[PDB]
Amino acid sequence: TLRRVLGLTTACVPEEDALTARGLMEDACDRLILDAFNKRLDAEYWSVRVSPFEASDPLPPTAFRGGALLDAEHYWRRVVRVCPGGGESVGVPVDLYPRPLVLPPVDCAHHLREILREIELVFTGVLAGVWGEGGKFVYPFDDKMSFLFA
Amino acid sequence: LRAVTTHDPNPAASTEQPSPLGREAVEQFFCHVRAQLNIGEYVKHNVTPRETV
Amino acid sequence: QTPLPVYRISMVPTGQAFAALAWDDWARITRDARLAEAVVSAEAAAHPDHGALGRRLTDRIRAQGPVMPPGGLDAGGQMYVNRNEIFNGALAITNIILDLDIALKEPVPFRRLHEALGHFRRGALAAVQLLFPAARVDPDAYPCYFFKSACRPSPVCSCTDKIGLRVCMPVPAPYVVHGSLTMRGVARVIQQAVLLDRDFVEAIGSYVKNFLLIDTGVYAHGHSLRLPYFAKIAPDGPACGRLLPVFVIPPACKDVPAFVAAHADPRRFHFHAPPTYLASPREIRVLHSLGGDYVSFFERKAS
Ligand SMILES: [Zn+2]
């Protein structure tokens, strides 16, 4: 997206260029979210890494029944997030259970919001630096594509 | 009542003015009510659809 | 293979049971209320009209269809007597299903009721066409399925004070409906469109006490709606009010036998039944919102 946006710059066009750039950023976000739907069932794809120096969800008791799988936990812990019922969104340590996993639907909305925050963090800076804007780049996740993972 | 008040007994020189009663009521309230009881206007005014392709 | 239908069953004399069915024997359920192809072909050949054809098909069904004898006290034999489908809020909706409750002050004949249904279908399709702009909804050949509840002890209708009907119509392609509020909005729009119609009021306005027809509160997570061909458990001891089809033939129907046989398809009266496409959906437009609430002009202006 940054390659395309900064390639459009050589067209020597006024503020209309910034509107075009905003359109491309929104299109890119839309396509990313749409392509993230086909991997809604993958638990390893959405799991995030946690170091011992960060706060994390408490370990479920069943994680203590893994056995020999608990030996390979030197530093990192991979945690995914699932929805057991109505708006609960509990955390699951992925690597502590034998394969295959039988889990409720993955909480893709939470992880996608976490990713979109970082996406907007760079898009807003690019917009404010290249064209000297003052408007923060916000993607309406809740009102556009939040129904897919509901 | 201010619109229909006079200040001169002579009918030719009376200071009566047209009453702004029917116009305001029909422009502020009854137009929306008329638009409410038509299906096309009701759909156009009362629902805001959102679609994803 | 999930997703699966989940049904709530009323148990006699008290209590409720639950079922989750991967597949079932719908042929057994609909066997005693199916018209043979020869009969419908002969009736269509004899009469080229559509109101008379529908009335005579309803007459032939009413004089034939028996009822299920009192089922066993077990939950495995009661689901064939009473069965209600539970609205699942995590699935898309591919069927507009309306629950019509007509409250009367005087009993209404059946020839008037057929005309009232024929005029209801005309306005419902206009509402659907307005709601789904990118689709094609022909108001002359679009299929709309009507079911009526049996009476309590041209067909005859001896209804005491109320009439129960179910109207099922597919969501036009390539549209889908998601959420509970969206279905409430669709039902409200359809009810308003059919109330603003003129012929329906002239047909049914005399016997009707109040013009609040469609209940929009039946769309919620965990809410159950009774299916056609299933009798409602009466409070005391019997099962009554079996929902049987009433054939309102479209004015431009090309295959009457297909329309008649489509009334026994279990996919035409389920909220989240899979869509019936021809080859493949190249694209689908999910209509996932219509508004927040009604809060009509009068209430907002009064506030
Ligand atoms: Zn009756």
Image (cartoon, coloured by chain):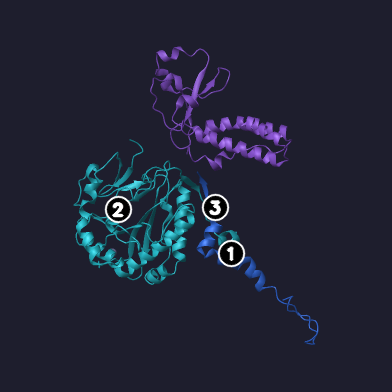
Chain colours: A purple, B blue, C cyan
Q: Looking at the picture, how far across and down is residue C159, in whole percent?
A: 29, 65
- Tag shown at residue B32: 1
Residue under numbered circle 3: B48
Viewer-nearest of labels 2 and 3? 2
Residue under numbered circle 2: C262
Q: Looking at the picture, how far across and down is residue A75, in whole percent?
A: 53, 14
> Is residue C103 among the parts visible in the rendering?
no
Q: Which residue is at a point 39% across and 21% down the rendered structure image?
A: A99
Q: Looking at the picture, how far across and down is residue C146, in whole percent?
A: 33, 58
Q: Chain of mark 3?
A: B
At label 3, which amino acid type do we have? Thr
Q: Is A31 positioned to the left or the right of C33 in the image?
A: right
**Quadrant position of residue C154:** bottom left
Q: Looking at the picture, how far across and down is residue B14, in whole percent?
A: 78, 83
Q: Name the quadrant where ligand 1 sits.
A: bottom left
For the N terminus of chain C, the image quarter is top left
Callout 2 secondary element: helix
Q: Chain of mark 1?
A: B
Q: Chain of mark 2?
A: C
Q: Are marks 2 and 1 in contact (CB under 8 Å)?
A: no
At label 1, which amino acid type do we have? His
**Quadrant position of residue C157:** bottom left
